[PDB]
Amino acid sequence: GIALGMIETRGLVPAIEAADAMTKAAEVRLVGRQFVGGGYVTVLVRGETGAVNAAVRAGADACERVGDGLVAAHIIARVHSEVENILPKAPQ
Amino acid sequence: GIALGMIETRGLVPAIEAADAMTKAAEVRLVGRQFVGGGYVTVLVRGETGAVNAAVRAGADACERVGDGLVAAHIIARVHSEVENILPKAPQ
Amino acid sequence: GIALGMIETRGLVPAIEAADAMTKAAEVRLVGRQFVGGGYVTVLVRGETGAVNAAVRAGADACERVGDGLVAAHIIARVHSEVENILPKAPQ
Amino acid sequence: GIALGMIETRGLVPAIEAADAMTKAAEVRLVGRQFVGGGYVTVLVRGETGAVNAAVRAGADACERVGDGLVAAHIIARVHSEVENILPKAPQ
Amino acid sequence: GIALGMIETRGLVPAIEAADAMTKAAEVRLVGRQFVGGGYVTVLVRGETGAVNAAVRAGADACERVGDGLVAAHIIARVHSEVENILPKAPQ
Amino acid sequence: GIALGMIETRGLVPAIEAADAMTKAAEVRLVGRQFVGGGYVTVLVRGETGAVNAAVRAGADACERVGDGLVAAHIIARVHSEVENILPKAPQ
Amino acid sequence: GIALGMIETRGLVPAIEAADAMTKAAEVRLVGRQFVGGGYVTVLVRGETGAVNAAVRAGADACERVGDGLVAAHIIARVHSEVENILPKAPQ
Amino acid sequence: GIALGMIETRGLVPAIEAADAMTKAAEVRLVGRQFVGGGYVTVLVRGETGAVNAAVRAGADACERVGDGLVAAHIIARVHSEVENILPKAPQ
Amino acid sequence: GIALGMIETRGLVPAIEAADAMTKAAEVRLVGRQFVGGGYVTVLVRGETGAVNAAVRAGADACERVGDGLVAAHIIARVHSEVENILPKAPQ
Amino acid sequence: GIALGMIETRGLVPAIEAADAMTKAAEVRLVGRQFVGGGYVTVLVRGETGAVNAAVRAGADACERVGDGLVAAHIIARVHSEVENILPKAPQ
Amino acid sequence: GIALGMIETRGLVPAIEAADAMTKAAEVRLVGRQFVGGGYVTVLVRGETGAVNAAVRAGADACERVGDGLVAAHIIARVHSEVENILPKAPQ
Amino acid sequence: GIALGMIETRGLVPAIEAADAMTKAAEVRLVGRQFVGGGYVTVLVRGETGAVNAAVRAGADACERVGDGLVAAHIIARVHSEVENILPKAPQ
Amino acid sequence: TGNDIAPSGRITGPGMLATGLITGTPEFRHAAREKPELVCAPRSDQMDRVSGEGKERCHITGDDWSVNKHITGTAGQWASGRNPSMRGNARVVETSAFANRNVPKPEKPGSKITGSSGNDTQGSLITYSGGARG
Amino acid sequence: KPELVCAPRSDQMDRVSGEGKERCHITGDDWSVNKHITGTAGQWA
């Protein structure tokens, strides 16, 4: 799907916990893990709206207490074609 | 094994101390060391779920009073396939 | 994939109200009613994550005040392969 | 008749009185009595919405004071096709 | 006679006491013994309306102080033809 | 024998103790062991009136202090010929 | 041996722990487990009187603080022949 | 593996949620879901001692907040051979 | 019958009086008289538990004031099989 | 069984009561009932140490107040081979 | 039997006295005597759990006042297979 | 396995009890019994880290109050390659 | 007397475990040895002994099957006392759905999720994998 | 008995965050080590 679920965390450890919970708790595809600088790490997953909604809920809960904690947990049901350029196509 | 043990610290001295305590403490292998940015440094190990638990606890205890200290200690007994794309395969 | 949504209630009357509301709200397949014992009744539905999300939410609202009450409402977007063996395949 | 009227009571004796009041009150056919467990007993009558509405109103009143009492008295004017699998078809 | 007399009790011992007392008290034939679940046991007799009243009152007093005690006592002078289906015809 | 001796307990361990004590104390044939549901377990013995009086007295006293304990102990010297249809003839 | 050791617990988790402790502690054989009903589980072991004493004490100790807890722990050094009809013959 | 992990819950919804969490958390095999009766529902997993320790921990945490809650979380690192006669091998 | 009623007296005169009264009082057959030694004579009867109860009571009453007096009156509703080896089958 | 358990009573009636209690309490085989003379009756049972301990304790309590009463209750775990020449082999 | 009875003492004179009392007391089979060093001497016996309990009590209270004294008296009802390698099967 | 667990006790009896508890609790291999000298007896087990953690904890509890006492319980999740020479491989 | 094998504290081992929680032991077997305003009375205030078609709430005058005190007969003493009985003391612990309507429960899950969620805090507690509020 | 099997969420925070958690009290032969067992962690690391 095109729905984008994004979780931002302070440090890599909560991000990997969030990504693990998100991909284990729904049928989402992990597309990117982008370091933002300032300690912020962001894990981006794509999938159907229902799947992304369940993943971000599972991700936010899993990594809220991990390490420094959570920054953001956001869901975009449909992503404009323009934003697709700034999003990572495949994880690295 | 498959379990993942992640220790996050501020600076590199605490992380190297933690990687040294983790590997010496239990039967684990140091998959990587990622510079998150803003200070945070994450050291990741892999091993049996029980070995990883012992290593991370020893790693956390070792580096909590070295430099700016420990930020996050973590264990993931089974890591989903997608997350493995964003994990260091082997140390550089 | 196929998600799982289940409503546990105290008594059959709340469960049928949940089963009616869940199936009317979205295109979810009612796969089983379980008499857990001691007065618990569970109704399980299968469908798309979005369909199951809307169904369970409608079911929880409908059966909240009906009879003795509602015990639990759960949605599992991705169900592990192992857990499939304990779930009813179709209602009887 | 599509409409379903169900009464839940604590013990069989209140259920039997509820069934009689419901069947005598209006033109409804008793589709089955279920033993949920833990003392719960449910009697389901089916008929036209008018007949079911009048019967359940009489049934809840009749069995309100019999034995441990009444737990639930519900009216569903239209039951989904999926839910009809979990409902009794004829009493046994 | 077609009048129905029911006595409900907590445990089997009070139920059997009540049944013996009811059968011995008046002209009523014992038709059923049901384990409602959760500790409730119901004993049903059929006979003349006047006879059933005498039997149930004797059984209510006989089993009032036996075991956990009497839950409900009920007499239905005329049972609707629909309800006859959910009543036992003879004891197994 | 014709006399019936019933002991009800709030478990199965007190039931087995009661059965052992009754069978050892007097000449009584254990005829049934019923799980009434809700925890209650009833043990019924049959024998001559004198034997049953001693057996039930022995059984009642033996199981009082074991487990949750004794709910009821009852002796029916002769049961109405109708009641014998609902009594076990031999434990399964 | 013929001595019977019984442990009654609330839930299966305490019972399986008791069975493991009982069999491990002494030289006794597990003859079966029974779901009494209403959250009661009874685990039975048969063996020599000396072993059954040691076994039951180990089982009572092990499962006292597990789950809901221990209800009863009984030792019948010799069970009358009649009680063997109600006791389980081999575990299922 | 041989180690056994067990979780007891009030109702089936927490039981299924626990089962999903255990199997997703670590490499364990769900070998049974048992209806103890009275509400309790037990889910049993089998695997390595390290894996089961992680699996049960994830199961307890996930199941705690779902439905009536969690009753027990138990590990048995070695299961005596006699006790395997009362343990499901493949789930029902 | 299996119930055993035995009276022990000091001297033979009370034993014969007790034996006469026992057989006169109830339907119990005299099974033997034992010269225990030291001036103790024990008379035993076998019959139904009620009959033996009446016989022993009548026997003890008759011989209480006869001769030296009465030592013991005892009733055993059912006597173990092994004990049958030492009891007299028929009087000498 | 090799352990020896002896009960000595003043009069035969307590001895038979002691034998009955001992043989019902545990798996002890009655080997002999000796008339010592002077009004002493000794009952000897041979069984395993646990069974002998349980049986003798039951025997002493049962015959403690029956008739003249008790003289001695003695348990010997193993009797020297030479002593077995002065012990009854089968009852008489 | 398989149970193990151990008595540890400070010296060899108490050990032999304990070994003598143990073997005479009950049906036990002296298996090993160990010089633990530093004055500790261990004597191990095997047999039925009931027999071992009798022997260890006899040995413990027989060797308590002779020599330096009794250090440890202990019973193991069932011994694991791994431990059998560290126990001395042959008499010395 | 690789994890090492040691329990050192004063005397042999505490050590045998500790070994039994350790080899019963978890899947560990009793690699050696070492009479250190002066009364110190060491039992070493090897296995997985989780198994050894449970084994050593169980052993420490078992032999704490047995005999002279426990000296030290020590776990090493992974011993150096050099240390493998001083450690025993299988017991004498 | 003789070779006592009773549990003791001096001799360590399995025999000393679970003291006081065990029953059937030789030690415990021994211890045991020792003008109304309305025709029908108020529905709420009165509860009927036999509820259906046998209710005494309504004062039915004239000939009726009610038997007064002076008339002895089938019910009461003549049915209660036919069979001897003994009422025991048991721990009546209800483990059921209704009994667990009030149980100590963990803190409610909270959702910090933003965006196209469609969440409603008002609705009954929906849960998602992990116990996260849905 | 404990009112809740797992200690309250915000009452504590685990040293090792996931699958090394200690909040949920798990009876049996788990991998917890009390003071009596020295070893891998502590001053030795």
Image (spheres, coloured by chain):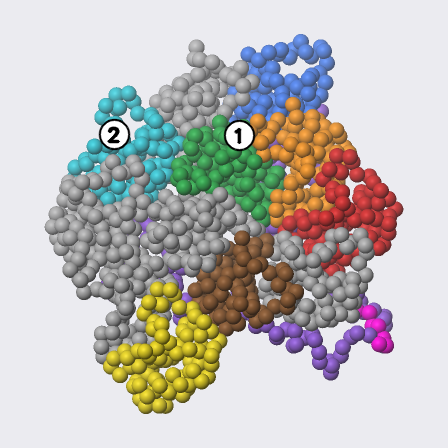
Chain colours: A blue, C orange, D red, F brown, H green, I yellow, L cyan, M purple
Residue L31: x %, y % from top left = 27, 31
Name the one closer to the observer, M65 or M43. Answer: M65
Q: Are marks 2 and 1 on the same chain?
A: no
- Whether residue F44 sits left or right of residue I10 in the image: it is right
Q: Residue at left 32%, top 78%?
A: I92
Indicate the position of residue F7 as horizontal and vertical percent values: 53, 63
Mark 2 chain:
L
Residue N21 can be seen in this image: no
Q: Secondary structure at mark 2?
A: loop
Residue at (34% x, 29% y) in the render: L47
Quarter of the image where the C terminus of chain M is located: top right
> Relative to residue D47, is residue A26 depicted above or below?
above
Question: In the image, which residues are magenta?
Answer: M57-63
**Mark 2 surroundings: few (<14), some (14-19) or many (≥20) residues within 10 A:** few
The residue under label 1 is H23
* Residue D76 highlighted magenta (yes or no): no
Badge 1 amino acid: Thr
- Tell me the subunit letter for badge 1: H
* Quarter of the figure that contains the N terminus of chain M: bottom left
| Number of the label disc, if any, that sits on residue M95 | none
| Residue underneath mark 2 | L90
- Horizontally, is L21 left or right of F16 in the view? left
Left or right: M124, with M129 as reference point: right
Look at the picture and state if A47 lies above or below H86.
Answer: above
